[PDB]
Amino acid sequence: TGLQEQQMSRGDIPIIVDACISFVTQHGLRLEGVYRKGGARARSLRLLAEFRRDARSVKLRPGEHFVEDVTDTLKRFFRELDDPVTSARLLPRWREAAELPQKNQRLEKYKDVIGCLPRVNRRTLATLIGHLYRVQKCAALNQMCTRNLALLFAPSVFQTDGRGEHEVRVLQELIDGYISVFDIDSDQVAQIDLEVSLITT
Image 1 (cartoon, rainbow, N blue to C red):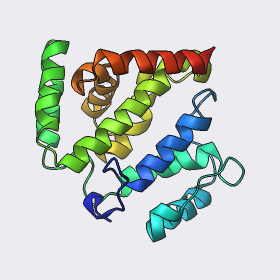
Image 2: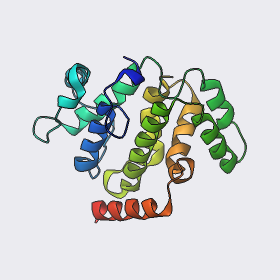
Image 3: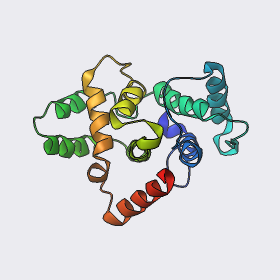
Image 4: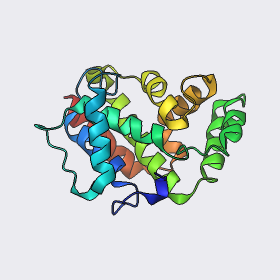
């Protein structure tokens, strides 16, 4: 049930993160309320168990699998990790970073804290943030702004279950600051802006 124990895609993140994120990228970015809390608890329970049985052999299909079940499965994967993808050990460091006065100093300090993560946590987190960055860029269609996403994901990502104001801020700022925090070059920036333009026009 540990992050490093998962079956890994060729990008070296867990198959389950890759498959759920890729499914939503293909079929969910225009849907209003994507990632909002709804659906059948039982169905994301069964889907998470199928990913745990053998992640490579799970094929998410637009007929069998509902978007909201896949989004709930992705959140539940992060909630049930033995160690939150943001490390439990590092939570005091995250909060100290969130309390710094200027935005740009907070972003540099987030990169410091991210460098304290094992590589697989860094890569998993980078994929998630980059995905939510695209979600919020498509908000004219799906109505999901950065703040909405941060509120929905912070409990699962940090495993604080809503208690702490800081975790919401960090996520909001990781997502808005995705390009700088994760060192995305301007070629990739342009490819993302074009892909979003295709999605929202």
